[PDB]
Length: 242
Ligand SMILES: CNC(=O)COc1cc(C(=O)O)cc(-c2ccc(C(=O)O)c(OCc3ccccc3)c2)c1
Image 1 (cartoon, rainbow, N blue to C red):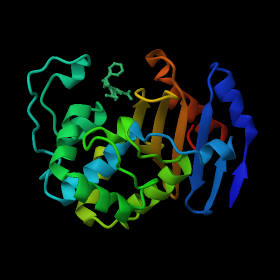
Image 2 (cartoon, rainbow, N blue to C red):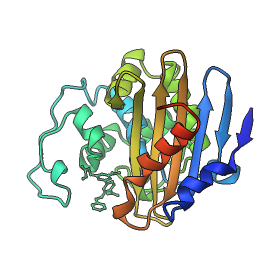
Image 3 (cartoon, rainbow, N blue to C red):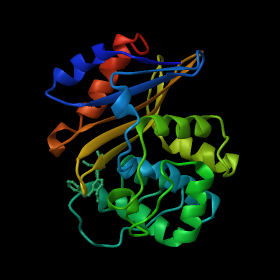
């Protein structure tokens, strides 16, 4: 049910890069990765944590729906797309940390820990600051654990309302055409070593879904586009996307 494919390493090496890609064929119920050890090593989730954070805020009513506007606080931050009003859709798309920090403060440590325990999310550990533990606290999750979480989400099995899960899957929409739909969430972990980039989600086909979770070493922000690029090359090699 798990199978290693060292050939994908060619795509990391081609870009002077290091990391892991994990795929899960939902229909056949089996998985593939270029590095079984790394696939199960636990990293900070960073902004991939916006998937559970969104689910929790929605189910608790911290966020009423995907249209509720979170007004820019007027602080001019380093990322231009952060210096504006957001809803849940745009906050997810632009990884607007300060919006989700407000969610986390509203959720609170007790509810947050209870929820992550209910989700079986990673090591279920929120130690650190209530509004940054997923970037520099004690929470950790592996690429394999990301897929297990993402499969519950896809099937509406997580303990939150089906409504919450449908809203978050809508907000995860990243790309779609006649050939496929990608629902995914990037992450960029820079506060604690090793600096890594993440991309987790799934590719929806006509008659199957391919879940994926990748992380890679990311010493500089200049290589952030490699998250999607290397993932897509793997997908093409496997004839999942054209
Ligand atoms: C052009 N950018 C956009 O449109 C959306 O902007 C982002 C995209 C992405 C992505 O993963 O791609 C990631 C972030 C992001 C995530 C976490 C933190 C954190 O606080 O740890 C963070 O800190 C500020 C920062 C500024 C500059 C360089 C490094 C860090 C930024 C922001």
